Image (cartoon, rainbow, N blue to C red):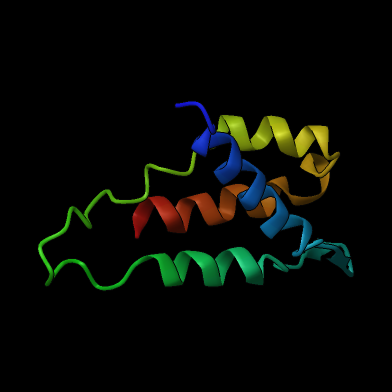
Length: 93
């Protein structure tokens, strides 16, 4: 509550996207979010068999607070298409 673990998580998830630095190839979306993708495939450790609340275990990372910091870093208009495309496969997974 004092060290703001949520602020640190937001900063880390924003750095994982600065590491992505997505661009565009022939005008079509190019998913460069490889770092965030691997982070999200690593956060899940097959908890369905281990009895953890795996169904709905990724409500930790938010969307609004990440989008505000993305606009502060000026990365919205660049990475927002892939942000929502990934938010679909991370809200379905």
